[PDB]
Image (cartoon, rainbow over all chains, first blue to last red; front, side, top):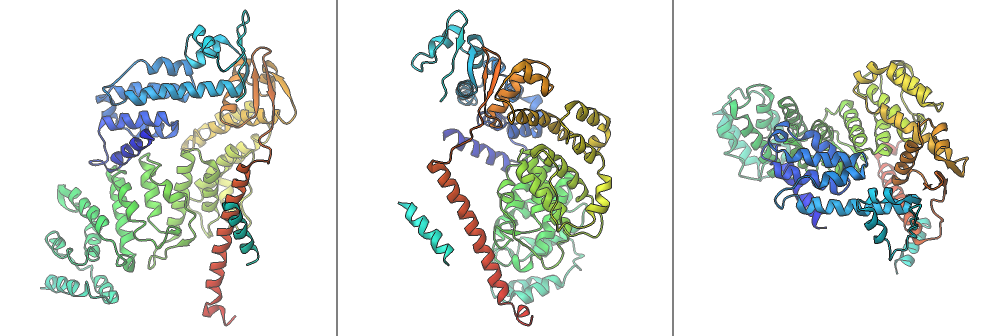
Length: 173
Length: 404
């Protein structure tokens, strides 16, 4: 909830603007927050409409778009590699750090719901943790990690009476 | 002393009612050759908010060139100020120069190539001039065009999700160009956000407008309707019966590449579709709808993989990437994974045996969630019927519907 309000404020501030063009910090915050909420279309259009002069002046937009491009191709190792390659001063740090947790949860849910037997290396690549950490993490969940073959087996995850009276009163006129 | 007479008459008429004579007086103008309106503009607008000076601003914008010297932006602020403080129903009494002024502002912004300052203006200039939210005005087209030229598709969503059911007469004017522009630009906006279920509907509304000639908004809307129908469904949906005969006789022959594209996208063969797309590259890139055809190409594989579920129960990845022509078990696995992630398919992947199992169980109808969904749909139908009954009762009392 604390991020949606910031996104709305950034959108309104960009829309008002001192002549259409907004400041680079709000542009970067908008792009990163679009990446957070899985608004790939909106992030792509925002990158399209950002002035080239702002892109030349501020080089962090390049890194944010690199992360967004890795997200757009659904390349989880690329996402995790490119997230930990740049930083700012308390402007994108909380949102860029919540992006990692969101990607982690998304990858874990996808592995749970789309697989019945996944190799340990592939699971570690999807999550981003090392292989031993990936295997030892799923202990309370009971995912039945195998040895030798290193196969991981994901586990599959009043007003009613008033409404009826309204329906009858509609039907009977 | 003509200016003194005009300002005195405006002051007397304002805060006195009788809008008819004020409208007649302000319409009895256009002889304003005196281009010193700047000092008389911010001298009479204090009384009775901002209901007058609309003709003055329209005259200022009529020049089309050298409006207010290098400080033209100042004029913009005036318009901005006006749009923020005009208010009242006095604007609706003259809803012919308001739309004209908005058209002039939109054209100026488009030529100036800053199509984002006005997005916030032709948003408070729409809900302040229209009767209700379900009334289509001639500024919806300008708002959609402005928020389309500058890629900001989010401001227009509250003005597109509403189903328009009345159309402003605007004291004249309002040709079919505004109707076509609104229902074409809204469809393009919805396509840009990958809302094909509603972009197809918007294009369909654009095509079936009554017509007696050919326009270049009903052609390059039929052409895009074909592509969106191929992307969303598997076939070109049939246009409604009440469609005009122009599309079925004249517009169709010009769209011959797209009918060939559909015919190839009628027999499941990605290679033939790629060959045809590459053959007709110039035609598809001249109309600027390139990248909507690559979506058809990438959707053919998804359609084939979905058709695989209607027959099989467990398919090898190597075997799967031989009936859909995916060239490798890894590409088939990634296609199935992407399809599962987006909810298009119900399947599970077994990397141990290298198989994919198809489940096909969306939902059993034994939960309160489906009860809530049914209740919401029934509420929508009830509101629809209530509106229909209101319209019929308003047509029953019509004196013209008493002699016949």
